[PDB]
Image (cartoon, rainbow over the protein chains, first blue to last red):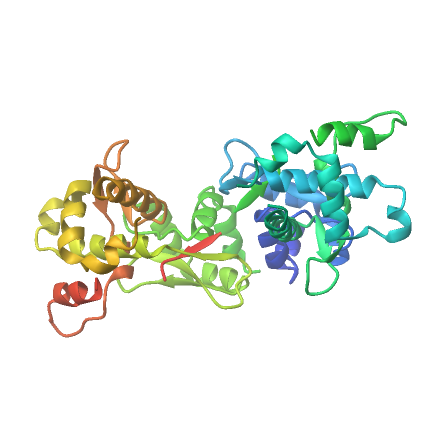
Amino acid sequence: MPVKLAQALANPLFPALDSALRSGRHIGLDELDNHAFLMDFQEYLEEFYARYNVELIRAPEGFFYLRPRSTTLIPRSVLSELDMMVGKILCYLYLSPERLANEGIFTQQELYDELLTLADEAKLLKLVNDRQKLQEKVRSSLNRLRRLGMVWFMGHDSSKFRITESVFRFGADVRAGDDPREAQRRLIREESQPD
Amino acid sequence: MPVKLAQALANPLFPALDSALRSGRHIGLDELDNHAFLMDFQEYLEEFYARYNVELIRAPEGFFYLRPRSTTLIPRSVLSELDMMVGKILCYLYLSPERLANEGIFTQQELYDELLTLADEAKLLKLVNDRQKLQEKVRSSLNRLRRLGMVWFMGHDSSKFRITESVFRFGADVRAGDDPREAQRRLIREESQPD
């Protein structure tokens, strides 16, 4: 192994960040130490994690994550369909023109209201067996998406949260200067992966 | 970091064994390369894994595993109550006087029959909502206990399996030359931990 790959593994930040990565957490800018850590050693941690048949991926929006190949040595898991939907609406909220002024801060109530109007009524209701049950499930997905590094809790509660640039993993594909919000709306209808 | 801690992490065995360890798998004698690997570097891998607030523990019966402290950086999980019971009966089967001659090989049918006679009828039946349903749940626990390194599948099926010395983690405490089998019978009535 190279010398500064050893300097990375020797850093007091690595065991906490290595575990977070292996659990599927996305490391955005808001974790400056961990983010700057992966910036200076990106070339070396890529080789290290490549030995687990996973790829340390830096998305074009600056955030890091591990993406496992089919032959990963770290067991993989998937987000539920409701969790995928909530993340997709979290990114619609991130695409909103107020996001710069609000710093990505939204309420669980704002997420409820966008979720009911933006999502297809037929499919969303088949993700339960109502609406106050759907609230406690949305709160469950947001805790899962907080663990993955998609939101930060503003308080001890899921009621106020800041959305992270890592939410772009739930965003459709866009180019030129097309409005990504309509593309997001049509889209809305161990290693835990958001696929 | 020390030089031969680097020789361990550089070994082509480490990423597969490191992942298996972090998932809670118990490394017994039957994995000779991985076992001999942890034998020659035990002093150095202890220090390495101690930085995740987990303890690389070698039980008195030769097998290795990671045991997380309350402040572990690797997320922890527990076995179900039925999985704990199946493992406890797997060790009762391991304590049997035929085990040396059979090399730890038992059938899923042998595990069913010992499970019904050895376990308390009132509690075991409250682990379902019958007996062919309990068979497919026993098969599920054995697949989980195989992942943890408690048994090896003799074939592509759970029908024939070899029990590992790591099963002693489900065994009661014994000293002098007392029969451990009666102590086992009274006992019968990310990091996944068998607690």
